[PDB]
Image (cartoon, rainbow, N blue to C red):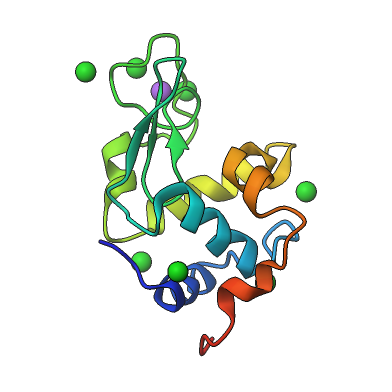
Length: 129
Ligand SMILES: [Cl-]
Ligand SMILES: [Cl-]
Ligand SMILES: [Cl-]
Ligand SMILES: [Cl-]
Ligand SMILES: [Cl-]
Ligand SMILES: [Cl-]
Ligand SMILES: [Cl-]
Ligand code: NA
């Protein structure tokens, strides 16, 4: 599924990401835009041989099992394929664990390089939330 911007904002808010660990909703939408272009089916291989899955590009090195990432963990206890669903529940629940892990949203390279320090409220401008 390719979400609309405000559609995704609404879904993320419903799932309690608005100000989760202090990150306003615009941060999450911005991260999703640059990670996946709001596409739940996005997959991208990393240099280390791991793969990033779904709307928030969650990595198989640490977070989900994809059966082909040697020496990896599965700390969200989920098959990576579940992160590609049109239902973002699994992605959001796993993201909550990631952002709580010590480094905040800096775990998302694209957030650090493209969203941090910017006017992230722009990403929810015009949305009925
Ligand atoms: Cl957009
Ligand atoms: Cl915001
Ligand atoms: Cl594996
Ligand atoms: Cl393969
Ligand atoms: Cl594990
Ligand atoms: Cl959803
Ligand atoms: Cl933080
Ligand atoms: Na893994």
